[PDB]
Length: 48
Length: 48
Image (cartoon, rainbow over the protein chains, first blue to last red):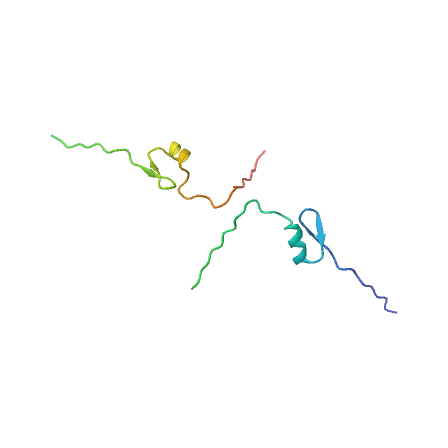
């Protein structure tokens, strides 16, 4: 009667063939999956 | 009797407050007027 299951937490794939389950920690020790070619990202502001 | 004049060759303004009458040499020894804030420019190819 009412068979149950428990699944494990899935793992996300970060850059340099590294995988983890926390987006905060996996980014801070392996970088993004796709690396930006260049150093600068330009931001514009509109307002007061 | 008519009137006549001869104008000098106009000067273009390159980067770093440098002015010259030739785009090629002026770009070769001064650089562009507005420098690219970055390192690389990505080129995509569509063809055979």
